[PDB]
Amino acid sequence: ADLEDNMETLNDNLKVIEKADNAAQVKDALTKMRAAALDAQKATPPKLEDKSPDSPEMHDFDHGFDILVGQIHAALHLANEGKVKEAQAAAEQLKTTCNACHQKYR
Amino acid sequence: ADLEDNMETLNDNLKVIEKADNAAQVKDALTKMRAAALDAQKATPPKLEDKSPDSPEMHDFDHGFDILVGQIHAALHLANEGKVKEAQAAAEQLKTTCNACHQKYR
Amino acid sequence: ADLEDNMETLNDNLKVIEKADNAAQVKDALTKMRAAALDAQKATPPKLEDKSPDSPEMHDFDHGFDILVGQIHAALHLANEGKVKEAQAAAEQLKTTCNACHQKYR
Amino acid sequence: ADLEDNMETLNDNLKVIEKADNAAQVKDALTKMRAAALDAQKATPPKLEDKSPDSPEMHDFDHGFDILVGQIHAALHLANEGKVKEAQAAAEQLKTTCNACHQKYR
Ligand code: HEM
Ligand code: HEM
Ligand code: HEM
Ligand code: HEM
Ligand SMILES: [Ca+2]
Ligand SMILES: [Ca+2]
Ligand SMILES: [Ca+2]
Ligand SMILES: [Ca+2]
Ligand SMILES: [Ca+2]
Ligand SMILES: [Zn+2]
Ligand SMILES: [Zn+2]
Ligand SMILES: [Zn+2]
Ligand SMILES: [Zn+2]
Image (tube, rainbow over all chains, first blue to last red; front, side, top):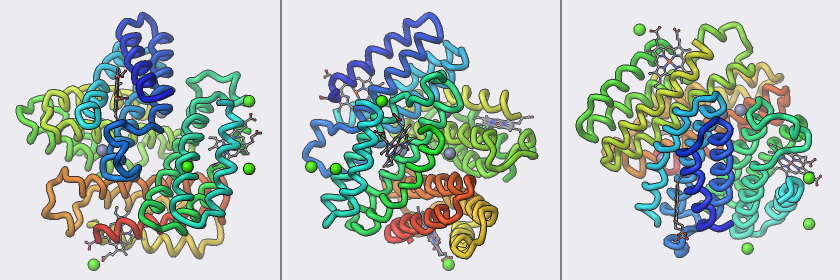
């Protein structure tokens, strides 16, 4: 899918995690986010489409998804350990990653 | 896409890179590899379909792709610096990652 | 420094971030957290002293540190952008990583 | 030790790895390179001494070590599996990383 739909799936599952009851739903949510993140990591934001694929700006953009993906990785460990509250706290915290990139390249 | 189709993409582009005349071709092939690895990374291999998403094997499987994507990342740096030869040698080098994963999960 | 002392440095600055009032203070503490983290990453914990330095356990142990440093790195971004509270929430959040390794390897 | 001592250690073990006759010798050499790389990663290079601690230059400097450490990580896996020739090829290939950072900051 394209950034749009991946960002959508990404955003949706954040709400799923926030309203999740058990670990399986959060785990399931994070997994879907992981998939959306990895798929979107190969796209080029409309504001950098005129920038070199490997310019200072694009390397930062790519770096951004790496951060998010790492945050989703750590979150999964928590959810896997049955730590639902900690996992939801990590989902909220990684929200800064979402915002930071948007401020820069959205 | 099916795990094998991504593997086919990975395999062919290794050839494209080896036969490349210029930086443009190595980068193009490297970027397609990045995309294939990332899609591959979301898949559940036949030999591990019985395991849980949270298991030493699946965590190791995921790690293998982080290794590959990171190597593709380094290769891309050399290519965007004009070092066509070094980028080609890097693609040759990461073949070891391909073999290492296969010996365990293929 | 040794593993044990770097851990102290880590815990002390975590409290500095908690009591911090400006971005300057948080950046400095995080900076120190990264150095003590990178420094401690080379060590072998007493719980795994007698075990292949290439064992599954040492690999997992090292992974835990990557997660920690990875989190400190993102927290540093926030701090560098002048987002005190956002960075403070990141320091809080990564406590979960400290916890996870301790229960398993300390 | 300082940046300079860590760089010497990196260079020595590169030579050890080249002449190594077995897997144990290579693992030992890579392990030392790992510690030296991580030790150096915390240092501010003379050429970046007047830059702000969180400037693009320092972020790029840090990224370079991440790459080097990742390459050592992959090489260790090779060595750990007894693939001596492959690990040595890995060590020689990462020399491109040594080069790239030197070109920019040495
Ligand atoms: C969990 C975190 C994230 C969430 C929940 C999220 C959510 C969204 C949403 C809902 C949109 C609007 C899509 C639309 O216009 O239909 C969007 C757009 C966008 N996001 Fe994110 N995002 C996240 C992280 C990121 C990150 C880390 C980056 C950059 C590295 C990023 C870059 C963008 C860009 C460039 C757009 C505009 C895409 C376009 O206009 O086609 N996002 N995001
Ligand atoms: C760039 C390096 C790589 C190349 C060139 C490559 C190439 C291939 C090829 C040609 C196949 C057979 C596809 C088929 O039967 O249709 C294959 C299978 C496979 N590869 Fe890779 N691969 C690479 C990296 C990896 C990595 C890093 C992993 C694991 C972390 C991996 C896991 C697998 C698995 C599990 C299969 C078996 C799939 C099945 O039997 O359905 N490969 N790969
Ligand atoms: C920011 C997070 C962390 C903090 C604040 C922290 C803090 C500490 C502190 C203060 C101690 C001393 C315990 C005592 O008084 O007996 C300690 C010991 C230890 N920590 Fe951590 N730690 C953190 C993360 C980690 C991680 C990520 C790992 C593993 C990857 C880890 C592994 C250990 C081990 C193995 C010891 C025992 C060392 C010894 O007694 O020889 N810690 N940690
Ligand atoms: C295996 C790879 C590497 C080897 C073999 C290596 C080797 C060396 C050597 C022999 C020196 C000269 C030491 C001296 O003058 O006392 C040096 C200097 C330096 N290296 Fe590396 N290096 C490697 C990787 C890197 C990387 C990845 C970076 C940056 C990300 C880097 C940054 C520097 C800097 C900044 C200096 C200047 C030190 C000074 O003059 O104070 N090196 N390196
Ligand atoms: Ca199949
Ligand atoms: Ca073909
Ligand atoms: Ca093309
Ligand atoms: Ca002490
Ligand atoms: Ca010198
Ligand atoms: Zn993990
Ligand atoms: Zn890079
Ligand atoms: Zn960064
Ligand atoms: Zn590994």
